Image (tube, rainbow, N blue to C red; front, side):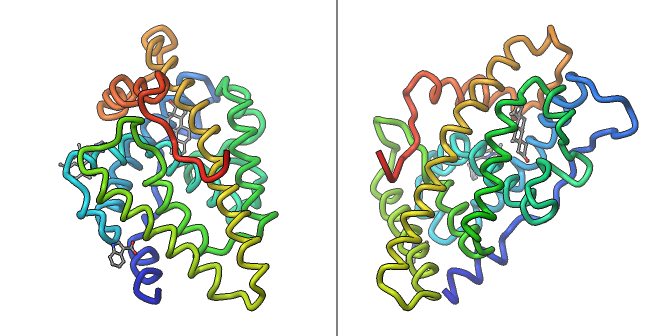
Length: 249
Ligand SMILES: Cc1ccc(C)c(Cc2nn(C(C)(C)C)c3ncnc(N)c23)c1
Ligand SMILES: C[C@]12CCC(=O)C[C@@H]1CC[C@@H]1[C@@H]2CC[C@]2(C)[C@@H](O)CC[C@@H]12
Ligand SMILES: O=C(O)c1c[nH]c2ccccc12
C-alpha cells in the first residue's frame, strides 16, 4: 500500500447473480442447483481475480490452478459472509442479489447447520469491526491457505508469496494503530478469524461431495467445472492429501 491496497481494491469482483427463480416455491433441487450454478459463475470471477493478484504469476502454471481449485470454497464463503454483513447485517446469507437465504431456505437446503456456521462467520465481521481493507487482504490470503501435505511443484515461490501477503496484512493493521499492543492484538484476532474459515469449508466440502454422489437421485444439477473439481480436487482434501494452513494450533 498504497500500491498493494490499490490493486486489491481494483481487482475486487463485481456483483454476481445466481439466476435463481424466486417466483417458484422453494425446493431442495432448485435451491441447491442455484447454489451450484452461482458457484460456477463465481469460479470464473475468482480465476480472473486470482490471476490479477500481485506476484500470482510467480507461481508455476500448475500450482496456480492448484491453489484456486483447493481454496475456491473458502474464498467464496468468506466473500459471501462479507456481503451478508454489509447488505443485511448478517440477518441472512447473501449468496447473490437473486439468492438470499432466510431461516426457511437454510432449512430447505438441508444444510442448516452449515448455514448457521457461515452466518456466524458473517457476524464476526461486525463484532470485530472488520474494515473493507482488512477484509480484502484476508481474502487474498485465503487463496494461499490450503496446499497438499507434500507441497506444490514450485513450493518456494508459494512460500514467498504467502509471506508477502501476511506482511501486507500487517501494514494494514499498523497503518491505523499507535499502540504496540493494539497491533499484536489485532493480528491475533484476524488470524483467528482466518482459521475459523477452514472448518466451515471442510463441512461444505464434505456436503457438496456427498451431494454430487447422489445428485442424480435428488435431481440436483452440477455445472461442468463444479462436478470436475468436486470429484477430483475436493476428495484430495477430504482424504487428507491436501490440508489448510492454520496460524494457530
Ligand atoms: C493454465 C491456467 C492458467 C491460469 C489459471 C488461473 C488456471 C487455473 C484454472 N483455470 N481454469 C479454467 C481455465 C478451466 C477456467 C480453472 N477452472 C477451475 N479451477 C481452476 N483452478 C482453473 C490455469
Ligand atoms: C460456494 C457457494 C456459491 C458462492 C457463494 O456465494 C458461497 C456458497 C457457499 C455454499 C456452496 C455454494 C456453491 C455450491 C455448493 C458447493 C453446494 O453444492 C453445497 C454448498 C454450496
Ligand atoms: O505484496 C505482494 O503480494 C508481493 C508479491 N510479490 C512481491 C514482490 C515485491 C513486493 C511485493 C510483492
